Amino acid sequence: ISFRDCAEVFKSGHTTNGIYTLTFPNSTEEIKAYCDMEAGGGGWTIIQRREDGSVDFQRTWKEYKVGFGNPSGEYWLGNEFVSQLTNQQRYVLKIHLKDWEGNEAYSLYEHFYLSSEELNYRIHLKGLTGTAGKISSISQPGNDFSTKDGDNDKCICKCSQMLTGGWWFDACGPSNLNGMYYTAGQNTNKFNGIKWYYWKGSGYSLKATTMMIRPADF
């Protein structure tokens, strides 16, 4: 069969990590997503993952909307799907980070959702906890989503063109998990890298990241 999200997949008995087929909320169109079932309680739908620098994240508004990459590795699932889902019910957002020294951390938001494309997939976050900072690394009141061909930030600049990747930039902001991938011998001092200010700072480019969602009622 097919499911609404990875939470439905796990609750239905499929408790192993892997690619599953989700279905869009009011229709039959389907989409593949990676499900993390063996960490943090499982039932997690991965919406973004970086782990090796294999995928180019300097994509268009359209690409960020429908999603790109491969679910078996690094990818972005799709803004449209995530918007539809997160406006179905209350979802939590978990952001897991890994540095090049073997350390890890995460930020958890009690409520997360994206507005329709009409409001530029503006992000909405509430209730931060976790080990990756006391202050949210994602600007807060959420900003519109910005891309190479979509300047929707609050900067007298083009944050996406200056830092690379699509993100909810402000006057850029303390984060960008979709920035340039830098390996261990060159991840220090890089402002266009993969950053989460309140854990490793603005110059430290991370080894791996994952953004995943799961309903609050899980």
Image (cartoon, rainbow, N blue to C red):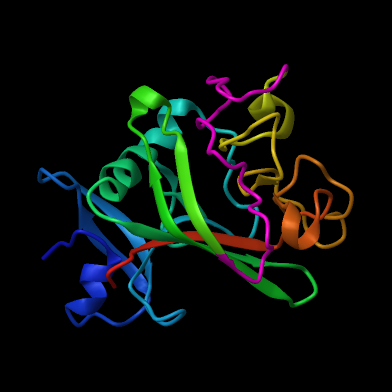
The answer to whether residue 108 is magenta is: no
Q: Residue at x 27, y 49 (%)?
A: 85
Identity of the residue drawn at 69% across and 22% down? 155
Residue 163 coordinates in the image, percent (x, y):
72, 34
Image quarter hosting the C terminus: bottom left
The image quarter containing residue 212 is: bottom left
- Using the image as rendered, state which of residue 154 and residue 41 is in the foreground: 154
In front here: 24 or 30?
A: 24
Q: Main secondary structure of the magenta part?
A: loop
Q: Quadrant of the N terminus?
A: bottom left
| Residue 39 relative to residue 32: left or right | right
Q: Residue furthest top?
A: 156
* In the rendered image, the vertical position of residue 160 relative to residue 206, given as above or below: above
**Residue 187: image location, x then y, percent:** 83, 55
Report the number of discs. Answer: 0
Q: Position of residue 103 (x, y in %)?
A: 73, 76
- Can residue 51 be seen here? The reply is no
Is residue 11 depicted above or below 87 in this figure? below
Q: Which picture quadrant has residue 78?
A: top left
Is 72 placed above or below 124 here?
A: below
Q: Residue at x 47, y 40 (%)?
A: 123
Q: Which residues are magenta?
A: 129-156
Q: Is residue 143 magenta?
A: yes
Residue 215 in the image, given as x and y percentages of width and height:
31, 64
Q: Would residue 147 be found to the left or right of residue 63 on screen?
A: right
Residue 136 visible? The answer is: yes
Q: Is residue 138 left or right of residue 91?
A: right
Left or right: 77 with respect to 139?
left
